[PDB]
Length: 156
Image (cartoon, rainbow, N blue to C red; front, side, top):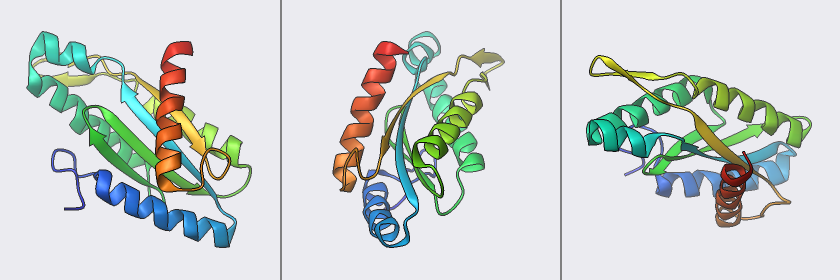
């Protein structure tokens, strides 16, 4: 019910619940809150060239990498397909602190993944939304981060 079966990350349901709660937390605490939408550059080609189990291997390894990097109170979810979300709760300069994690995420998702005695191309794109300027509700931040992902994929 609260986890993505394939990867063990949060699912859409639990993401939305935890993001809504995080907004209330940070409104009171003064912590920074950012939503990062991530997708994989070569998921379609893995599925096309090596079948559905190859794309799955990409998803499983992405999740493993995200579980290594994202610790409470931050959290990670897979929505569906190759679309992932990371919610960062942190301190300090909000645009900087989110940009710093974003950079680390891109780096960690760059390395290929072994599959069936071959290596599959990884690489990711991401978009960032910051509370409250990019939205004051979970849904507003979700949507804005997805738009930011679109913009990032168009511009690089």
